[PDB]
Length: 150
Image (cartoon, rainbow, N blue to C red; front, side, top):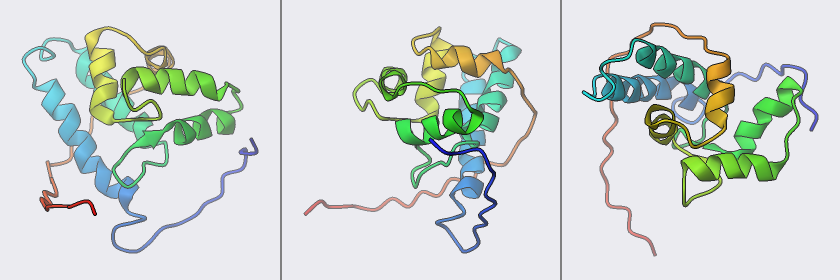
């Protein structure tokens, strides 16, 4: 749709608008846990793509769970000018999420890339293989609570 101009909306509160900020810790946790997993602790390109994906994952909106739907993912392509059909996005994400279909998670995307390939989105992700080397200490908000469904 119409997304070309960068509207600089600025958040500033405590938690809601700070999703993009707070999630970095989580992203670094997830990279590190896969990086230091004995299976993946072998490839030099391995930590690189972890950070590359980390860089790119946060380029999306990142919902309340740090998740990305077929909507937020397509927000990227429409902003960048590259058009695709929703059926394609849903196919790609439905590959990663397997049963969900419309929303994927950061570790699942890594399961798919680090496994071998299943979702074509790996191709576009690793096409622009830009990385960094950042680190942020594992700060996990446990928040273990019993959420009973009415």
